[PDB]
Length: 310
Image 1: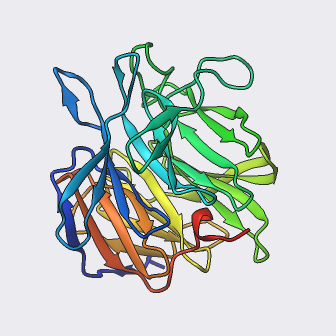
Image 2 (image 1 turned 45 degrees about the vertical axis):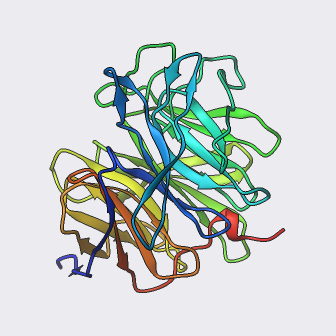
Image 3 (image 1 turned 90 degrees about the vertical axis):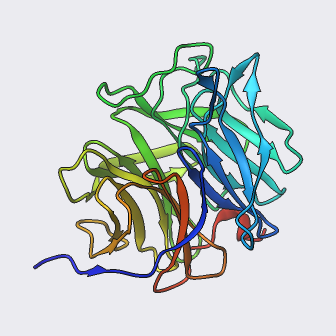
C-alpha cells in the first residue's frame, strides 16, 4: 500500500519570525511563539512573542539573557497551576517565563552535577513532570554546539519536586517530544523524535523521571535532509509529526509504526506544531518563510497539561 495523503487548507497567521518555533497557548487562550534565530551584533538574542490572532501583530514578551549571554528560546509549554510558560532554551537550558516578561533560569546543572545542556522541545505529562529534549551541548558560557552529527543529545525530566534529571543521552539531535497517556490519565509512553535518523523513539513511563523499555516507535518517511521536528497528539492519541524538509506532517496511530496518513504542507520545512485548545485547529511554524500557519485537523487535540484540572 501507499500512505494516504490529504491536502487541507493552510492559512498564514503571522510572518517574519526568525526560526519560528514554540507555538503555545496560555491559560487565557493567548498565543505565543518563539524566534530562536534573532541575533544582534552576530550574537544570540532570541525572543518570546505574543501574537494577536486577529491582526497578526507581534509583541515581544521576553528577550531572555543571563550574565550577558542571550537565549535561544525554542519550545514552550504552559503550566497548569499558574499562567506561566516553561521554555526550552538552547543556550540557557530551561526557563520559566511570566506574561510580564520576568523570567528565571531553572538549572545551571542537573541532578548529578553535570552542566546543563541547551534544550529544544518539552512536554508536560498529566502528573506535572516536564520531559525535555536537549540537542545542544552545554549551556552558556560554553560555545553553542548541536548534535547534528555527534550523539551527545540528551533527554531530561524536570520533576514536580524540582529535580532536573538527565534520563537518557547519546541522541543525534533529539527534537520533538510528547507523552502518550492512558484513558484514565496515567502517563504511558514518552515519544522522542531523533531528527536526522528518521526515527521516533518511545519509552514506557514508570513514574517521575523513570523511563524503561526504550525502542524504536515509528519510522519517518524520506531521505531528505531533516526528519521529525515538533509533534503533538490529537484526542485519539494519533501523533502528528512535523517532518522538516519533506513538505509533510506525518500522522501516526497510537501504537506507532509507519505513518497511517500524511498531510501535505504548502512549504518544505514544518518545524513545530500545537493544537489550539478545545479545537481541531493546528498551528504550524515553518522555517522556509519564518511564518506561522494554521489548518483544520479531523478532530480536537489532546488536552495539554495546562487544560487539565486537579
